Length: 460
Ligand SMILES: CO[C@H]1CCCC[C@@H](c2ccccc2)OC(=O)[C@@H](C)[C@@]2(O)O[C@H]([C@@H](C)[C@H](O)[C@H]2OC)[C@@H](C)/C=C/[C@H]1OC
Image (spheres, rainbow, N blue to C red):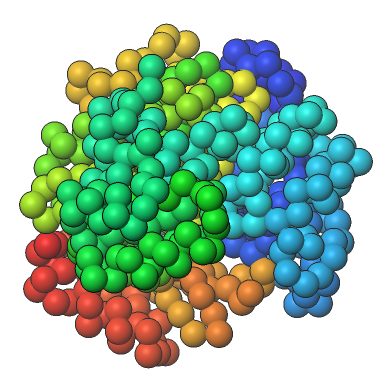
């Protein structure tokens, strides 16, 4: 029951270095609502004051007119220009201006908008405002495929066969249609042709298509180095959730599997499809990759997992994702709260949810071995999340299942349902009961059919 009186006192007593008590959310809809609800629950527990951390939000004319819920939920709101998001939520310069003027001490971008633009943390730090996300230098490194892949390889993180295979740090590009055909022959089709300076990209399904498509890329961005990368045929997408503080520690929070797809239609946590011993290496690979780029906050290492059992690095998504509650549930970690705490300079082993996940005492101050732990924490139960289809937010409470929750939002409606159970089967079964309630209809019939097939219930 450790509580304190103010954020100022929390920072001091938990080993941090920066007081954050007002945050600007550069987002709307479910992102804005989730951020505030997670952090206020944390402020309540820590400060006995749910409003100890104050929130300012950006609002477009379209969101105002709709009376989007997150407007009144916020402590203050700022009207911003309408139209495409480069005029509002993805406008780095606008975001920094507002942040600086209020002032707030931190920005949260969530997912979408400028959440992957390195220029955001860059310009914020330059103006003394914190970011609940990675620093620009980390984002720049993971930002482009080639450097990202070469970083992974050198760290022993397996990468897909590509023209730069073998390269290492302490000519992965082709020049001609003829050099390209040679490299393509070693790599195999289907494959990606990408000019490293672009788009400027083409999928070559065979070697007969290679010349035209390669030449197209050369025409599109003349002079740019071209690289070739294998496309995984019918691989699973697996994600490792990592959390990294400002002191060089990163911890994994198991991972998620995309067991149905071009949108992620169904996602699960944990990812049970892979043997635990290899997923554990996938986790350790993500930690090391995060550490060497200087990653801070929440991020996802995305992997391709094939049926034969091979996995390959795909990318580091430098932001929290909308499906993060799957992970939050099986790990019992409040992720937005963790980001806020980390942006205040609290180290991972002083995060109370991290200590509890690791069988330590909640307020202990002892360090924890995160990279290859001896007895790794166990995921708590299992979560299924399903995307439902066709900044205003409507929550779904199900009288049929106390362990299912979801929402749908208008920019036709997209949204997600989340189902927990004590195991994978209980989780799938709770989801089916709720979707059937939901049909008080076309996408649920679609999802119910899918969840009821032998193939899915046996996961392969
Ligand atoms: C927009 O607010 C919604 C978001 C619900 C997301 C789905 C749900 C869930 C996940 C899997 C299966 C079933 C349900 O996640 C949860 O309840 C859990 C994991 C979690 O997000 O709860 C929030 C925090 C304590 C923290 O972030 C995390 O706890 C560690 C609280 C503030 C609940 C808020 C909700 O509003 C009432």
